[PDB]
Length: 253
Length: 261
Ligand SMILES: [Ca+2]
Ligand SMILES: [Ca+2]
Ligand SMILES: [Ca+2]
Ligand SMILES: [K+]
Ligand SMILES: [K+]
Ligand SMILES: [K+]
Image 1 (cartoon, rainbow over the protein chains, first blue to last red):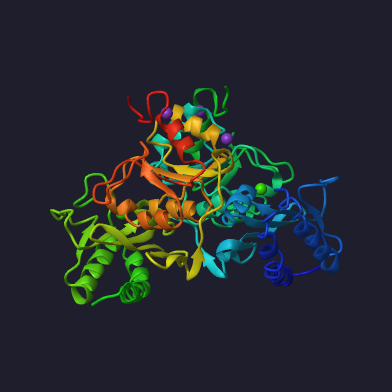
Image 2 (cartoon, rainbow over the protein chains, first blue to last red):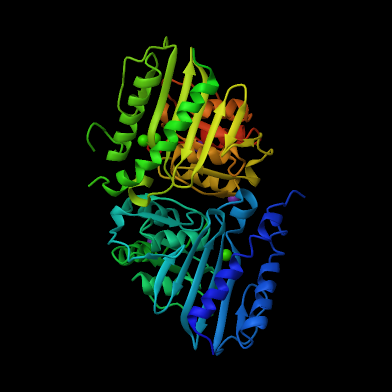
């Protein structure tokens, strides 16, 4: 079976030939029309058959038996749907490859800004092919944090605002997560991801020495997904502590 | 002896050379000086200086109102530039992305040329009275009509009472924040956001938006719905025509929007 060099080589070429499906979808002058891509999912289903006949794909509808597959791809063809629909910007393609359950390749493609982030085990992380280094230490009071504030209880919201440097939000799990990997954000939180919302993220967190865990501090199952944090190492513990304090982060009423 | 064409051309020339200056300034950035609450860096400081040198060479009779200047700026100035050398300074410092340069020219009080320069994303927005508004030379038309419940909004969730923040959460489609006023405003201009709110801007935070708001048929008012003096600055909204009073009605309701009351 194939080398990561050969797989990545073929993946990068495939992504670069989806500039032939979005311009058209950016149409939407009649969504929903976004649900149907999905074309993207199915076209990548074709790429696997053509190239990697034993590889399987986990994506939004439909899968089915998930453990234990040798060669597994997990995809969000469009992460940041509201952004694509409302903004035509700040959305991305997420792809991740797992071998015997080990993350081997990850991609986050910021198609609107022409930025491909890639993670390769054995080589490192890259953005348009220039090597990403471990971000510098970020304490919570020195960092910008990103989360959905409409979905947490007000007191937990207040406390995050007070303990952080600032708050921002891009609105695509994949992009808010790259801002963490890049040192731009100290942490990103998602209170209800699907496995494809965070699958690429594991290898970047590993290769760039980030913490990526559940909100209870535990290791995440890539096949199932969980309320999740990706964080700079110097502010991981403090964010979790704010989230879990005074009976937790969940919003009621 | 200067047409708007000729002025735009030198400004465009000035903007273009700043990319041989900024990368080096980002590298030696930066480690509070002359600011009460605002952040400042070597980058803002040099860009301002460089633009003052521009006016000295091409437009010696024009005045500059900017983050570092305060000057005594009578409403009887014929040719005035209001500048934000870097808008989104926190963004610059922490992220090196989502900051912009803001320039606005006013002739006897009337906005004539406006520039919002998204340097990290090389998108230049400009508006020219008589020609229209442009994003990288591509013409901007009025954004499609957008109601609150269908629109994304942006604002600082940290400086309003949380009950106003909730109502606005409920009434809008979603919420995002870029974190530079000029950029969150340009989102409203191209129909990406329904509205953007700054509760306490300075003239340079909003100078360029007046002309974009006229030409793109946007609503740009105080949070009372009134005209804004381009020389003083008041709590402000820049909004799609269709969600403007809904945003203000929610903001002004239940005792208003201030955090401490
Ligand atoms: Ca998603
Ligand atoms: Ca500034
Ligand atoms: Ca500013
Ligand atoms: K909490
Ligand atoms: K809502
Ligand atoms: K209110």
